[PDB]
Structures are given as structure tokens and as C-alpha cells.
Image (cartoon, coloured by chain):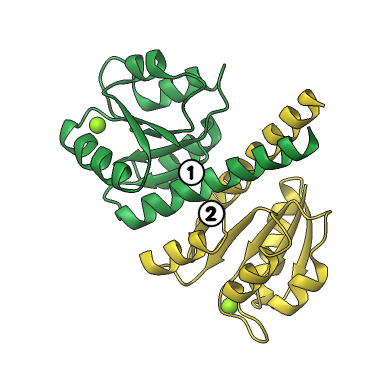
Chain colours: A yellow, B green
Amino acid sequence: NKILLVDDDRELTSLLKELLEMEGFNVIVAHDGEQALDLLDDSIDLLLLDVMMPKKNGIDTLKALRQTHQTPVIMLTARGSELDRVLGLELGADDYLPKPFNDRELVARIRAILRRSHWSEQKLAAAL
Amino acid sequence: NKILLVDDDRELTSLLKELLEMEGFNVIVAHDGEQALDLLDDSIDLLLLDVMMPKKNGIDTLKALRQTHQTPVIMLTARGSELDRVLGLELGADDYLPKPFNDRELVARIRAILRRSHWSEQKLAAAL
Ligand SMILES: [Mg+2]
Ligand SMILES: [Mg+2]
């Protein structure tokens, strides 16, 4: 399972890349929305998307990717108000996890949406 | 879209039934884990599941339903610790929203998982 980490905080992306790699994931990192959309392809199983970033913020990245991709996305951002959360979810995100977060909850939410993805694939392969 | 509302609090289930009905959902109510499993069938698109309930708690209900059903479930409970959240998600829940909650966020999270369900169905019908 391949995760695209989109966050402009290099310290967090390095910590998360190591964590998710320890958890058995293939991780690719984008540092803005522009980079993200350039790296986004069919091989990506999930996006961990930050909101406030230079060049193209996460809200605009999500709006753009959702025009062509149904790829699962989890917003992982310091923007944690009820408004921020409802906006992310309504714009196309499958989950929304504010910062600061617990690593165990992040992994559990990654696994929750990837379990749903696998069930969808199994049902599709069963029907085919 | 049919929602199965599993909670022992009659005051909350009545408030939520009205809210979700105003939002265009068909709502059926269970007051414990035993009638939740009795009411659970293929017509149910999502479960709003409480934890602390008599006869059968939400954790045991989730474990039981997940043996036979892949139906989307959102834990809606006063059990909001990191442990509670990670446990719910690892046991089979698609989302976990602690109490007290914001009605707008609940609806947004219901819509986020039902949008994923519809995309899965559209892809399945497209492949068929
Ligand atoms: Mg940032
Ligand atoms: Mg209760």
C-alpha cells in the first residue's frame, strides 16, 4: 500500500515516512499541492494531505485531485476547527485528523479506509 | 440511504432520527447491541453505533456484525480516549466520533463514507 504524504513540514514528513515504513507502507512525499498533483497517479492508495502550504494549499489540491481521482484522502492539519473538518470532508476527504495527533490513531484511520478499499476490490473481483 | 441508529439514550436517538430525516435519510433505531444485530440486514447502508449499552455493548456488537457484514459503521460514543478510538477503528469501524459532537461534522462524516460507498457501487456497475 502506497501513501502520498503531502506536507511542507520536512521534519514531520521524515518522522511520518519512517513511522509508516515501519508499519509496512510505501511512502512518497510532496511538499506542496503542485508537487502532490504531479506525483499523484494510479499507484497511490491514500493521500495524507496538509492544508496550509506554499504554491497550492491542501483545500485547492483536494478540489483539483477530486476532479480526476477518487483516491482516498485524509486531511492531517493544524486546521482543526469544526468548520475546517466539515469543509475538508465536504470537499472530498474520507477522513480529517487535526494536529497535534496520536500516531496510533493516524495509523488506525489509515488502516480503516484501506480496509474499506480492499473490501471494495474483493467484492469487485468476486463479481468479476 | 438507510441508517441504523444504535444507542440506549432515547432522547438522543429521537433528536438524531429527526436531524438525519431532515437530511434525507431513512432512519431505524436500535436501543442495544442485540436488537441492532436483529435489525441489521442488506438494506442498511450505515450504522451509528454507541459503546456503553445494556445486554450487548457496541464493541461486542461491532465484533459480531463484522463476522458477517462489511456495512459501514461510525462509532458515536462518549468513549473518546485515543485508546477507545484506536480500538473502535481496529475492531471494524470506518470512523469514530466522540460525544459531545457537532451535528454538521456528524452529517459530513456520514456523507464522506456514503460517498465512498456510492463510488464503489458506480465502479462495480461500470465494470459489470
Ligand atoms: Mg503546513
Ligand atoms: Mg449509552
Q: Position of residue A3 (x, y in %)?
A: 74, 56
Q: Chain of mark 1?
A: B
User: Residue at image x 52%, y 21%?
Assistant: B42
Q: Amino acid at mark 2?
A: Asp
User: Residue at image x 52%, y 34%?
Assistant: B72
> Farthest residue in the bottom direction?
A55
Whether labels 1 and 2 share one chain: no
Figure quadrant, ligand 2: top left
Q: Amino acid at mark 1?
A: Asp
Classify residue A119 by image quadrant. Answer: top right
Classify residue A111 by image quadrant. Answer: top right
Disc 2: which residue: A95
Q: Position of residue B7 (x, y in %)?
A: 28, 30
Q: Secondary structure at mark 2?
A: strand
Q: Secondary structure at mark 1?
A: strand
User: Residue at image x 27%, y 25%?
Assistant: B53
Residue B107 visible in the displayed image: yes
Residue B95: assigned label? 1
**Image quarter of the N terminus of chain B:** top left
Q: Chain of mark 2?
A: A
Do the CB atoms of the residues marked 1 and 2 lie less than 8 Å apart?
Answer: yes
Placement of B63 over or under A83, stated as above or below = above
Classify residue B119 by image quadrant. Answer: top right
Left or right: where A52 falls relative to A98: right
Q: Nearer the viewer, residue B93 or B104?
A: B104
Q: Please tell me how crowded label 2 is: few (under 14), some (14-19), or many (20+) other residues with Cα within 10 Å.
A: many
Whole-number angstrom distance, CA of label 1 to CA of label 2: 8 Å
Placement of B37 over or under B118, stated as above or below = above
